[PDB]
Length: 542
Image (cartoon, rainbow, N blue to C red; front, side, top):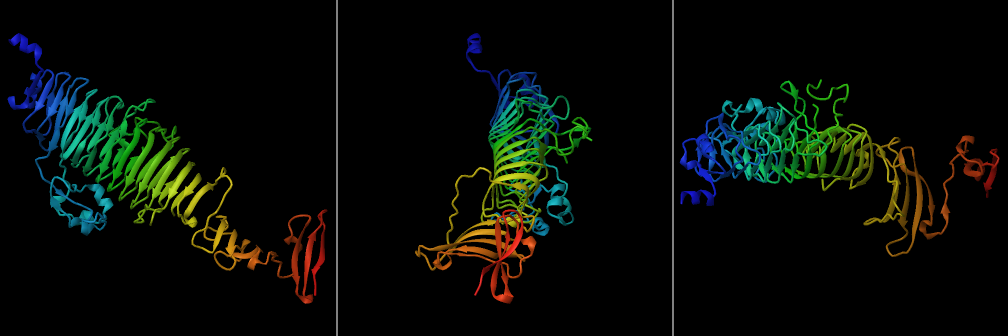
């Protein structure tokens, strides 16, 4: 029977049969069932002998610090892992019962409680975010560093599915072709919740966060260090949801970490949602002189050819910036940012294109100077602004297609144009007139310089209106104007120079300019003949 049984049954060892996780790992052949809670010490390392294992978790790994898994064979899968710290730290909760953000340091300090969730451990980033909190926090709530971390070290082709936990962290160190799939809402610890760190060895490649969600944590929900997906864009974040990150939802690191670059290239950031981050929704910048990366002489600061594939992202409720990035030659599309306290978008980009961007009700707390900022020479095609609450400062950018109840005086761009509209109709609701206004921002950002109006003659249903063409004079909009059909008179009312017209008032040949000669109660006409010569004629008299 043993011979027969050996060939007809599925192989699996279970933790309940061993004293240590390493003993179970050593006995494993195909499956490994975690069927009892396991308390690990920080730094506890397990060697899986290069075996391709299917680890099924039905219990918890309990401990502060890192549980390190090494030498898992390509194709290994870990499902249902649950990390939980032994320590219950002091956490702050910077939002109210009505879900309003608290920004006052004293109000935030008052939220202090010991819990493994529904808040996060304060860190130095909070000292910046809530000014004065550093001196108000009691010493036992400062400098905590609690995280129960599953560290996968130097493995290739390992996937972690449906992971969860309390004060939990997941670290892929020196890994390639690994994925964090369908994270089952782990509540974060002090460190970033999902980290792909490749500071040593080759640049990380094939590393993904696919689906799932995370909540809380003192740092960023998903973050990458020194990863390059290649032209194939093999890596990134797709279909992910981040809620209440203590820092940012998704972050590609910037600058030097250690003696090398922590920057990232060629990754995908698509179909994801970030809600209520304490800092930013998506922080996709690379620069904050670049050891291990392109020299500043090759690519100036904020002008690296990051080449990320960015599309279909939604951000809501950030206390910081909704969408931030830098880089040159980027193509960004279909971004929707709503209800943010700081800028909806902060773009330190150059020679980049932004298509179909919607920035709705951001910078609601005036944390920044504008709702959307773009530093370099960029192109914006389709920009929706204003919800129900400068708006845009992109000094060197060319924009087309803005929609929304924007205040024109709050727009600053290099060029704004609608080159390809068809025949147009201006429909006016709730007013006695319809209007097409012109504003030359060089002359005035607050006053319209001219207009074409249509005004009701009499009342509704009169079947009569008059059209008027105006011009600003003495900083008074519509100061001068020509009218057609005022009071249904069916004639044109023409403005004339109130005094003797100077020779230089007339512009073109074969034109005349009426002027008033008060001393004779006569209208004269300065005429520029077809040949360019001026002559003054009598136009109307008593």
